[PDB]
Image (tube, rainbow, N blue to C red):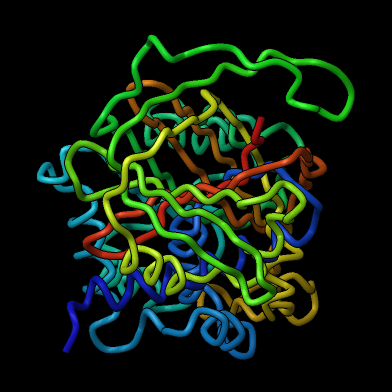
Length: 379
């Protein structure tokens, strides 16, 4: 039978990709940096603290159950394999669950959660709001190596906050073949919707894995693979052959196995690779996407079944968000993600931006884990 971590990495990445798809469709050329893996680990934890119909909706949409035989230890081997020194490039993943200090938890929840995620529920008092907020925001900051600070704004946590699930993902990798500082030049007027801008540009001619893709509607796209020096991870780039062809034609069929197939049809060709030097910070609200995928109850105050955690008081998720920050330059890539599911609070309206974009995917090839995805501008 297949390698457990690979089976799980696919299920996760597939689910994570399906939610990115929803995010993309909910805009035109939305410039969004997402983390398929990060949204999947939190929802796996949310599988325990939830119950009944609500749990079943989560499991259906995810394709698996952490409580199933093998699933849990498998998923842990995956983290270990992604974080090993042998990858050269660095990925770091940490999950946490902060629960209201006085909430009466169902017998067995805590002992069970530990035997699955090998972690203990951090119990905090949400009454002293600014202290609780600091406690978690500081946790995110140290686990994203200082990249994501202030995951939580002021109206994000109040005395009514009973639960908060968090995932912290960090990726620091150097290009196998760095771009030369020589070809780094500014480009003008990215045709930005409003005015003129000076977009730095990087370029290099070398041998890159490449394939030519054609979407079911007869649209040509050229997929290019750009390796990181440890050879376990790479960034796939996808841009349409012709500018009239909308990127949405690709995202609407995009899947974890499609990316798999892309890899399986590439050849080391000589190409001129031009890539814009960027830093993109983005925060997504995952309510609509998760709902669209079929997980409605958890958002409804009267139907959100959180009985596997506490029968004391009814609970429902108030906000589901993901904050991603990424930096692509001559030497490499440094990205971070903080996904959080919060019980009772208010979310500062979702940030949306549009422009002609290109797709990118940061993947761990051995396991098939897509860590990041995006739609950055294309000058």
